[PDB]
Length: 57
Image (cartoon, rainbow, N blue to C red; front, side):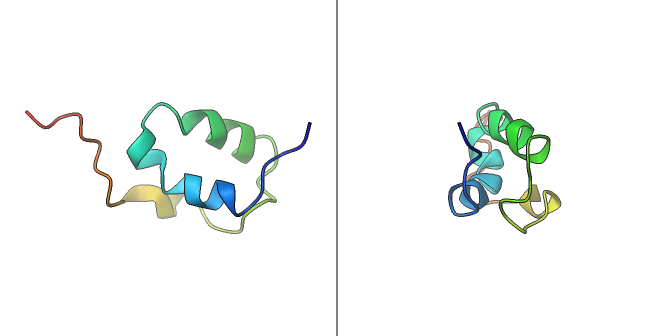
């Protein structure tokens, strides 16, 4: 159909830390399918407020 928008993708970029396995589907169809959407880097998503919440033991 058509790539997403910089409004939904942008908020999804930093969500890569909260999703963990889900956002990988976007980063692939975004950074390799047309990253012209947003203007923010991929490294910026190195830290977020939503920890992995996986290794909490």
